Structure formats: C-alpha cells, structure tokens
Length: 208
Ligand SMILES: CS(=O)(=O)c1ccc(CN2CCN(c3cn[nH]c3-c3cc(Cl)c(O)cc3O)CC2)cc1
Image 1 (cartoon, rainbow, N blue to C red):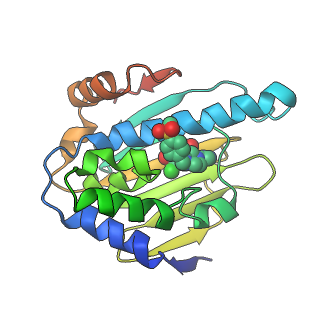
Image 2 (image 1 turned 120 degrees about the vertical axis):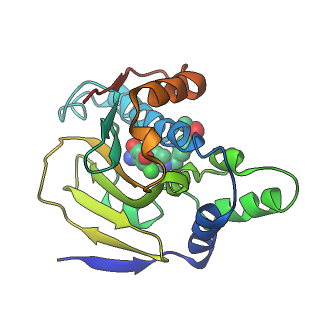
C-alpha cells in the first residue's frame, strides 16, 4: 500500500496561498506544466547525446494534452526523463523551500502569481484549477510510481501498477467543479497557443 508524507512547512505554505488568493488569470497553470515537461525532455535529450541507449524506453519526445470531460480530468503526459521516487518526494525535483522564499518576498512586494515559474515552482499552479493532482512517472533505472495530493498539507506515494509507460510523467488534473472550461477544445488551443508556442516539442491536443 500507500505511504504518506508531510509537505515541508514552506510548500504547504505556498499551496494555501495558491488555493486561497483571489486571483483571476488561473490559465497560466498550463503554461507551467508544459514548461516543466519541456524541461524534462530536454534532460533526456542531453542524456542521450552521450549514451544513446537511454532512449531505449520509447525514443520519441513530445507532450500530449488529454482532456476528459467525463472524469473531469485534464492530463499532461510527456516522454521526458521522469522522476525517481527520491525525486518525487523532493517536491518533484524542485528547489521549493529555497524557491518559495524568493517567491513570497517577490509576492508581498509588488508582483503577481504569474511569475511562479521564475522561482522553480510552477508545478503547484496546478492547484489554481485542480482539486486533486495525480502524478505518474517512470524513469529508466527505477520503476513506476504514483504521487498524489489534494493539498491539506500531505501527499501519497504508492508504487503504481496500472499503466506501464516506459518513460516520462503524467500529470492528472482532477479539476474543480467550476473550472470545466479547461477540458474545452477551443480554450486549451487558445491557451497552448498564447503561452507555449515556442516550446521546442510537438504538443498534441487529444480530442474526445
Ligand atoms: C523550462 S523551465 O521554465 O526552465 C523549468 C525547469 C525546471 C523545473 C524543475 N523540474 C525538475 C525535474 N523535472 C522533471 C524531471 N522528470 N520529470 C519531471 C517533470 C516534473 C513535473 Cl512537476 C512535470 O509536470 C513534468 C515533468 O516531466 C522537470 C521540472 C521547472 C521549470
């Protein structure tokens, strides 16, 4: 079964500011998770320049956007390097304490939540729109895991035995009842187009 972990003080701290703040431009969250995957594929590509059998676990590199109007999920899947268990636990490979500090000195002092990726913690903008995030990751040398949180200042990590994926990371947004517009064809295209045009990797928008 299913170990539970506390979010460090500062990361729990952040999250509640995200959940709680009145802030209207919630759409940046997709910019942020895109930029993250974009960062992970970069890492496996560099990694393959020296050892070309790292790409043994699926050799094409892309971001898929999969809306599901039925389960209220939107899922942003990539074939990037992936996280090991160790990573997942470390705020999903982010600097977080370090990062959040900078963020809030920049926050309380004239600058909005949209600059959150400039501090290395874009992931959490997920909670602008999601009431529960599930994160699926496989990385070559480890096995596959599921990280999950609905905030509340904790998170699960199970080793997951649903889908094999060879490599990369699946971020499932189980979206808030009133944010169903992010399952919309029109809206996701608008957003992926105005905020992630020059992401150097093919972004496929799935249709339903
Ligand atoms: C492109 S960036 O704006 O320069 C940037 C760079 C690095 C990060 C930090 N993070 C480190 C570990 N990362 C990683 C490694 N394996 N898998 C991931 C990964 C993580 C998340 Cl949270 C995600 O949504 C997708 C991923 O592929 C990438 C993102 C965030 C933004």
